[PDB]
Amino acid sequence: YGLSLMVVSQRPSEVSDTILSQCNNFINLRLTNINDQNYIKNLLPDNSRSISEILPTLGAGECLVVGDSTPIPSIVKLELPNPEPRSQSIKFHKKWSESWRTPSFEEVIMRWRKENG
Amino acid sequence: KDEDIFILTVQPVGIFKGEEFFQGNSMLPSPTEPVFLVEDDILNKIFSNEKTKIFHLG
């Protein structure tokens, strides 16, 4: 019917094996856990397992590509996108270095009861 | 051959270029390639971040 899935994860050993068994193309970044490496090796072909020993030593921007679309499993260096994704934290340490601030409790004790509850 | 030779075993931890440190190397040295020890200042530079809200541990 024309539908495809891209599954992104950082703990492969905690995802269902039913869905990960339908994957044909694998992009692997740095991994430092033995269980994850063993699971990936079991999922990956033997020739990739021979070169899989480079997973703990992979740097920044380099990924191991394995699958049918490539003639040989390889190591590829990518380039940064433009624009770049970014999250929104509150920087605990940076805020803790400022002066003392007093929140307005009168306003925040409201909105617990919008009109009468 | 009645001569003493001192041999060492080493394992890499990263690669640095210029005056900054990055994790991971993905490249390995070849035979006939020099080694140049290390100085105490570069360790201080690596383990002391430039601002970025440094927190001293020990």
Image (cartoon, coloured by chain):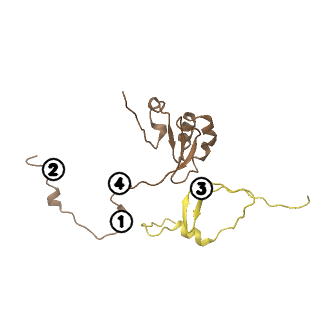
Chain colours: A brown, B yellow
Q: Position of residue A46 (x, y in %)?
A: 62, 35
Q: Quadrant of the N terminus of chain A?
A: top left
- In front of the other: label 2 or label 3? 3
Q: Is residue B23 above or below residue A43?
A: below
Subunit ID for the residue under disc 4: A
Is disc 3 placed on a helix, strand or loop?
loop
Q: Amino acid at mark 3?
A: Asn
Q: Report the disc number at residue A2.
A: none
Judge by depth and name the residue closer to the eye, B52 or A6.
Answer: A6
Which residue does the numbered mark 2 point to in the structure image? A112
- In front of the other: label 1 or label 2? 1
Subunit ID for the residue under disc 2: A
- In front of the other: label 1 or label 3? 3
Q: Are marks 2 and 4 on the same chain?
A: yes
Judge by depth and name the residue closer to the eye, A69 or B19.
Answer: A69
Q: Amino acid at mark 2?
A: Trp
Which residue does the numbered mark 3 point to in the structure image? B25
Which residue does the numbered mark 1 point to in the structure image? A94
Q: Is residue A45 left or right of residue B34?
A: left
> Which of the 4 image quarters holds residue B41?
bottom right
